[PDB]
View (cartoon, rainbow, N blue to C red):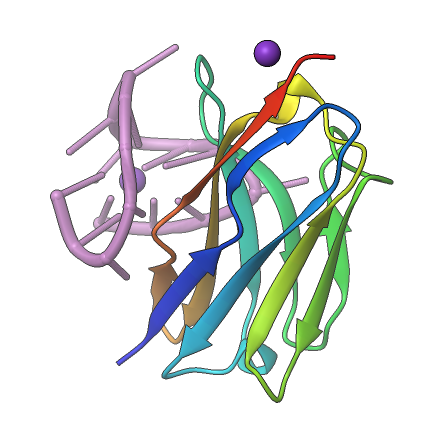
Length: 116
DNA sequence: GGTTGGTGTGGTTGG
Ligand SMILES: [K+]
Ligand SMILES: [K+]
C-alpha cells in the first residue's frame, strides 16, 4: 500500500543547514496534499509546511524564510531544506501524505541543533 | 493506535 520514508536527521551546529527527505511509495505526492510537522521536546506538535498536489507551498511563521519545500516527481520524494538552524528547531520532524480518506505518516526523524 | 506523539478527539489533521 502507501508508505512514507523519512531520512536526513541528525546533529548540526546552530547556523548550519540540512535537508530532510520524505519518499513515498504507493501514492504520488503530486496527487494529494503533503504536510510537515515537528514535535519539540517540551512542546505540542506544530505545523511546519504544506505542499499541495499542484506544488504550491505554505510555511509556518517560525520557519518562513529559512525552510523551503521542493518536490522531485520522478523520485516521488519531497524535500524540506532547513537553513539557518536554531536550537529552537530541535525536534522530531514528521511528514505525511493524504490519500483518499486516509493520511499516511513517515516514521519521524530527529533534528538536534547545538547552541553556538 | 494507527502507517505517527502525546498534556491522545485538537492540532493549518478524523475519530
Ligand atoms: K548545545
Ligand atoms: K491523534
